[PDB]
Amino acid sequence: MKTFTAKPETVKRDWYVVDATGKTLGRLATELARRLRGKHKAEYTPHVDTGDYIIVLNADKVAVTGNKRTDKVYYHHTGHIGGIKQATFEEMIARRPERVIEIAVKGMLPKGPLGRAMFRKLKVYAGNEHNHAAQQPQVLDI
Amino acid sequence: ARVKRGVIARARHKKILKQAKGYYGARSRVYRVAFQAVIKAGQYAYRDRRQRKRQFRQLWIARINAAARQNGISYSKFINGLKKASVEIDRKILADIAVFDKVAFTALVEKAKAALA
Amino acid sequence: VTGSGKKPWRQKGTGRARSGSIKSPIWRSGGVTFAARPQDHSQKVNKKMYRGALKSILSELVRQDRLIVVEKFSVEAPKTKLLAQKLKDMALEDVLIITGELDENLFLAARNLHKVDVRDATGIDPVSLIAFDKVVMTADAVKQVEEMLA
Amino acid sequence: AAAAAAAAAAAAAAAAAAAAAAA
Amino acid sequence: MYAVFQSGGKQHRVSEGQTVRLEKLDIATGETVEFAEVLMIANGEEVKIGVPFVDGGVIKAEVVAHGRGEKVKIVKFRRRKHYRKQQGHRQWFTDVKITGIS
Amino acid sequence: METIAKHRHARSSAQKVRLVADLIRGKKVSQALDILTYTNKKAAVLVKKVLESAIANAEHNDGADIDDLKVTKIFVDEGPSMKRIMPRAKGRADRILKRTSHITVVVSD
Amino acid sequence: AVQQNKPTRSKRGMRRSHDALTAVTSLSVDKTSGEKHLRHHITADGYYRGRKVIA
RNA sequence: CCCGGCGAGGGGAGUGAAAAAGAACCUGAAACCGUGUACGUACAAGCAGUGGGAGCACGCUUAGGCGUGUGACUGCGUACC
RNA sequence: UGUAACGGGGCUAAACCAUGCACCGAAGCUGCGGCAGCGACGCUUAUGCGUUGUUGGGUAGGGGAGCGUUCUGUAAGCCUGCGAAGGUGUGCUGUGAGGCAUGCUGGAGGUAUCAGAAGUGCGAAUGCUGACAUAAGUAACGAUAAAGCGGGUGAAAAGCCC
Ligand SMILES: [Mg+2]
Ligand SMILES: [Mg+2]
Ligand SMILES: [Mg+2]
Ligand SMILES: [Mg+2]
Ligand SMILES: [Mg+2]
Ligand SMILES: [Mg+2]
Ligand SMILES: [Mg+2]
Ligand SMILES: [Mg+2]
Ligand SMILES: [Mg+2]
Ligand SMILES: [Mg+2]
Ligand SMILES: [Mg+2]
Ligand SMILES: [Mg+2]
Ligand SMILES: [Mg+2]
Ligand SMILES: [Mg+2]
Ligand SMILES: [Mg+2]
Ligand SMILES: [Mg+2]
Ligand SMILES: [Mg+2]
Ligand SMILES: [Mg+2]
Ligand SMILES: [Mg+2]
Ligand SMILES: [Mg+2]
Ligand SMILES: [Mg+2]
Ligand SMILES: [Mg+2]
Ligand SMILES: [Mg+2]
Ligand SMILES: [Mg+2]
Ligand SMILES: [Mg+2]
Ligand SMILES: [Mg+2]
Ligand SMILES: [Mg+2]
Ligand SMILES: [Mg+2]
Ligand SMILES: [Mg+2]
Ligand SMILES: [Mg+2]
Ligand SMILES: [Mg+2]
Ligand SMILES: [Mg+2]
Ligand SMILES: [Mg+2]
Ligand SMILES: [Mg+2]
Ligand SMILES: [Mg+2]
Ligand SMILES: [Mg+2]
Ligand SMILES: [Mg+2]
Ligand SMILES: [Mg+2]
Ligand SMILES: [Mg+2]
């Protein structure tokens, strides 16, 4: 007997809110990636996103230990010849403070179509006020 | 004797092309490339009759890990608790129970916890 | 193969294959690669082997009960109508009548029947003595073949 | 009528080397 | 009210009145097999786990039909080294129908 | 009744005629005759003649009215290419191909 | 200057997708001579915007 | 007899066992080129398959069950001599 | 060329040490069937019936067992116009080369069984011939002496005739 395979028409999704005013970036992002792939759900399948929508309010006070707030650097290539742009942690915070959590979970998540779908279910905010209160999201200690 | 060999080649190439229907491109109309597609496809079938059991072992293990952490135990502590309570229920059955009928899985979790502690 | 002897093109410097005779067995209207010959295929069975085979099938005919023995075979005039009449009287369809002595009237009467065979006891052969279903033997032919095999 | 003006392609004449050769 | 039972290595989760597909039992074509190695009964939060077998339990079943399963081809092939090898296989399977559950 | 009309060994090539086929595959026949009147290719001449023949056969044999007709199916198949030789530089020949088409027009209501 | 592999009928159909024609949209039917012609073009009989200009 | 250019080619009628035997003529395969229908395909990376697999449509019945066509998504997977 | 000397996200442990307990982890081993070979040993031999232990990755190569095609004998026998070969589909079956049955097309041959003989099996030889692709409806239309208008002809005139 072919065991259970969760059909994407009948699987249901919840809504979670994560506080991030001092969580460590790597551990927080790993737990976001775990709930986003859906591995807290017993109807789990690889080829079907059984994930859960996660709203990370206050995504700029994510605290990083070590000397990483002045030493951890981020690289992205433009596409031209000399274009290797590079910004530290505090400078990436000062430019666009949600890109840090988005790059972290975009590193941890799978790659390709389903990985980009699981990332599409992750929307983060640099403040304390979201606009998805019509969804009834529940808080989650993560 | 002069064995003319049209019909033999037609029968053989028809068998291989019928095996190679469904494939993209010239790999379902050309014979010289449908033979490579057939032989490489049979090679992958021979590898995947071993790989399917690997993949489904990992799928059952992931599902039991998810249901066990929903009931308050890790998977390794779960399986050691089951072997210490002397249950031989394999993990295909465990994962199918974990999806269909979850209160029996809570029964398995409490018996494993009472064994391990 | 009736052709030329030149190379159809030069060896190096053309985008075509290497080729040096238009007669070649890989070409079109080239030779057969391993062409045959008028030959002789006569297998040589030994004298005692051939006689042992004839002894074997005569013993097999008498064990399988297919060698009807008669004192003589005789028709008056060479009428195949009378020969088929006589054979239907004797109740046979496929029949080999190997003769004690020479009967040219039976030659003439069996030349046109398409199932009956008339021989000598000397000129017998295992293909005939196996293939024909009911072998009729003259007692004089029995004497001649007991001489012939001894 | 039916002329059928399709004679066979006897095309290749010769060649040469005539190229800057690495040597 | 299902039951999990073991028939030659592979374990099955079957309910009453189901059919299931075992590997070839040496039992005649219309006879009943009574499996003894019942490992789990479940009756709507009325479970009892076998340790390693349930004591009070058998599973009765009738052998519906024997047969040979789907042919699967096996091609071994070593590239550039002049060897390939076709083969066939057809497993003998045996359908049983579960009636008794305890 | 679907009335068919063919033109075999049309002296043009299939890839050229299939454009003017794809223009009017599916229309009504009067509007298709307008389109093939004011389309300015040689395939318009050819398929306009074949649509004239198909309308004429459908009205005369089966006896249906001209407004009812509608080009359900129309296609252009490859035909027997005739093979000439164009001589080109440095002695080499080049076999050039003169292709042909089998133009089929189904017309019905 | 010459190709490296043989391109599929998929690629050939995709390239030929653009070379297909567009029809003439709608012929102007002249008011007083009832016949079709192109926009701003004189007809076969010779009319254009009503009057016969030509022989 | 009709379309057409008093052409080519076709459509009906006719001989015909057969015209999908019509001279470009028995059988009529494959590459190749189209048409009609079902499914997929315009956020997507690579020997193009294979294991899994939802959906859709078409065929069947102790509704259950399936097959046949497709294959989104996914683990593996760097042609042949 | 572009971080680029963890594989990557990232980690002050998710680093290193020392002691464990668990688990994951291969086509290994065990379980369940299935096939073959080689050994033992009795048998009850149509010369393999019951077990039995053990073996089966494979190039060059050596050995063994077969399938299929054409023709000859078996064959003036059998199937076949109530439809043979061949072609195209499906379903069953065989360890594989394969085999059988059938629906459509075809319109006259085919051949069991056991033997015999081979021009006996194609994917590769810059192989040979035929056919059809591809580049592609792309380059080109062959002197940079040059054309334009009216009238005729026709279904159709830039090129023909005036
Ligand atoms: Mg021959
Ligand atoms: Mg095909
Ligand atoms: Mg394993
Ligand atoms: Mg010489
Ligand atoms: Mg010749
Ligand atoms: Mg010759
Ligand atoms: Mg002698
Ligand atoms: Mg010259
Ligand atoms: Mg190359
Ligand atoms: Mg174009
Ligand atoms: Mg005519
Ligand atoms: Mg032809
Ligand atoms: Mg004939
Ligand atoms: Mg024909
Ligand atoms: Mg074909
Ligand atoms: Mg899409
Ligand atoms: Mg691509
Ligand atoms: Mg599958
Ligand atoms: Mg640099
Ligand atoms: Mg383990
Ligand atoms: Mg093993
Ligand atoms: Mg075994
Ligand atoms: Mg071996
Ligand atoms: Mg013969
Ligand atoms: Mg028929
Ligand atoms: Mg033959
Ligand atoms: Mg046939
Ligand atoms: Mg004949
Ligand atoms: Mg080879
Ligand atoms: Mg070749
Ligand atoms: Mg070419
Ligand atoms: Mg082209
Ligand atoms: Mg170009
Ligand atoms: Mg250009
Ligand atoms: Mg140009
Ligand atoms: Mg010129
Ligand atoms: Mg010029
Ligand atoms: Mg003029
Ligand atoms: Mg001019």
Image: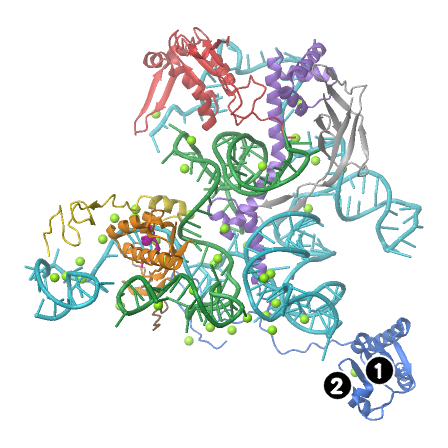
Chain colours: A red, B purple, C blue, D brown, F orange, G yellow, H green, I cyan
Is residue C50 visible in the rendered structure shown here?
A: yes
Q: Which amino acid does label 2 sit on?
A: Asn
Asked if residue F17 lies in the magenta stretch, the reply is: yes
Q: Examine the rendered structure and indicate whether residue I103 appears above or below residue I70.
A: above
**On what subunit does the disc labeled 2 rest?**
C
A129 vs A44, left or right, is: left
Classify mark 2: helix, strand or loop: loop
Residue at 90% over, 84% down:
C147
Number of callouts: 2
Image quarter for ligand 1: bottom right
Classify mark 1: helix, strand or loop: helix
Quadrant of residue C62 within the rendered picture: bottom right
Q: Which amino acid does label 1 sit on?
A: Leu
Q: Which numbered disc covers residue B84?
A: none
- 1 or 2: tag closer to the N-terminus: 1
E95 vs F88, left or right, is: right
Asked if residue B80 lies in the magenta stretch, the reply is: no
Callouts 1 and 2 close, C-beta under 8 Å: no
Q: Decide: few, some or many residues near mark 2? Use Cα within 10 Å; few <14, some 14-19, many ≥20.
A: few
For the residue pair H66 and C53, the one nearer the viewer reads as H66
Q: Distance between the residues labelled 1 and 2?
A: 14 Å
Part of the protein shown in magenta: F12-18
For the residue pair C149 and B19, the one nearer the viewer reads as B19
According to the image, label 1 marks what residue? C87
Quadrant of residue A113 within the rendered picture: top left
Q: Residue H42 placed where, x, y %? A: 39, 33
What secondary structure is the stretch in magenta mostly built from? helix
For the residue pair C105 and C56, the one nearer the viewer reads as C105
Q: Which numbered disc covers residue C112?
A: 2
Q: Residue E81 placed where, x, y %? A: 57, 48
